[PDB]
Length: 155
Length: 155
Length: 155
Ligand SMILES: Nc1ccn([C@@H]2O[C@H](COP(=O)(O)OP(=O)(O)O)[C@@H](O)[C@H]2O)c(=O)n1
Ligand SMILES: Nc1ccn([C@@H]2O[C@H](COP(=O)(O)OP(=O)(O)O)[C@@H](O)[C@H]2O)c(=O)n1
Ligand SMILES: Nc1ccn([C@@H]2O[C@H](COP(=O)(O)OP(=O)(O)O)[C@@H](O)[C@H]2O)c(=O)n1
Ligand SMILES: [Zn+2]
Ligand SMILES: [Zn+2]
Ligand SMILES: [Zn+2]
Image 1 (tube, each protein chain N blue to C red):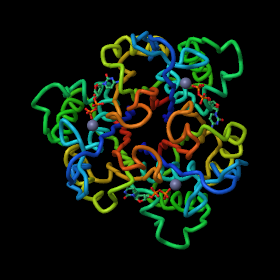
Image 2 (image 1 turned 120 degrees about the vertical axis):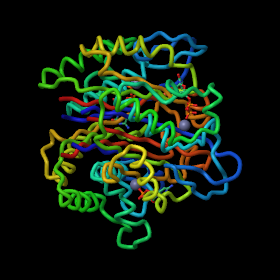
Image 3 (image 1 turned 30 degrees about the vertical axis):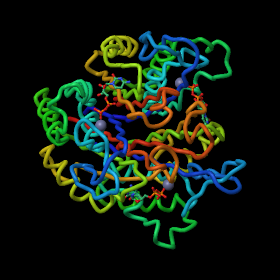
């Protein structure tokens, strides 16, 4: 059993929607990023790479490499997962916590769990996603951006 | 073995004391919330629900439902725990990290561990609580609110 | 198997370099602290003490005690580890996430893993360190300080 932890942040910028956990969520503003800025999947990817001792998302897929521009975070998720499995690991379970004042993540979580479980080739029960606001405090409370944390357990 | 993670924040507002980890801690200002605003127990609850793949505190006990107004966070903690156990889980251990510039949590932690272990029906040794300031940085460093993180391991 | 979580923050102040994960990293400003302000090792220490139910770094090594002034965080790391092992624990694995806009931690991570694994008497593979910026948001995004999170799994 191996434990991992990931954390990510992306700033709001431009027009909506935003992509979180693979879900296109309607919002007044979008998120600024090289890729699709999916904070939830970056934090998850890092948690999994962390538990595998493979480093982090930026070590494997550089901000500098042009191909990663506009990149689908689920692709990165699946690749990191491919490499993790090849190192001999299997999924224990993952838990994600989206820290955002808005939009409301609640209704999109079921679909998120479907995408993530698909990507990790596991059952939805091994995947949990949740959300919380920082009750108007901070860059998140001010609507400046979204953050996300995640933990993973590999076997 | 299943892993979970929780995170919560509540803003200062009104008169003291504050309730953290179930402990009434004297402070110049109190915390604003629908319930008692116990940041430590919300973060813990989410960590446990997360490890169980039951979602989050707000999914089980809505901000909208009036009964939860003024609600004792230990009640929510015990209920979430009831449901978790019914899903077949048993406690491995939990670790909580209170992020607050003040007040000093240190002297109240023993009592916190007593309440939490009581609520989870475990031994104090399976429960750990700690604290840290953000050295004057951020909404926490500015005394605007308190945050808390927690991880849990279920069996 | 026992899980732990740690979190720490230190403000920039003075002249560089900074010490992170035991590595002297050149930077325009340094970090303000009683000790060497190694955010990465404090967060790690707490994660390990947390998994062991030993509390936190400040419980074991007080800000008030003068000896800890200028103190080498690896010393504290090794001591906390000594005490943890004496309580009967063995390392499962640790994962660290440095949240800093700058400097770039990437090139110093290998050396960090060497120091940490040395200190914990484990193999580098049981140690992972990663980094992330908060994309210009927050006290970290503003260059006001560095934060760090860590999780640990004890056996
Ligand atoms: N202080 C920092 C921050 C990030 N990094 C590295 O560079 C990348 C950070 O990029 P980022 O903070 O923009 O995160 P994303 O835009 O990939 O979501 C990370 O993936 C780390 O590998 C670093 O070495 N030092
Ligand atoms: N961006 C967000 C934030 C929270 N939520 C949900 O709604 C609740 C958040 O309420 P909250 O941030 O005020 O936390 P508490 O006041 O219950 O401590 C969470 O329990 C989540 O279920 C969400 O769907 N999307
Ligand atoms: N709100 C708080 C914050 C910290 N503390 C305790 O006092 C110490 C916090 O000191 P700190 O936030 O300056 O962290 P460091 O300077 O040791 O890195 C922690 O080690 C906790 O034991 C507390 O009791 N209540
Ligand atoms: Zn990202
Ligand atoms: Zn709360
Ligand atoms: Zn520190």
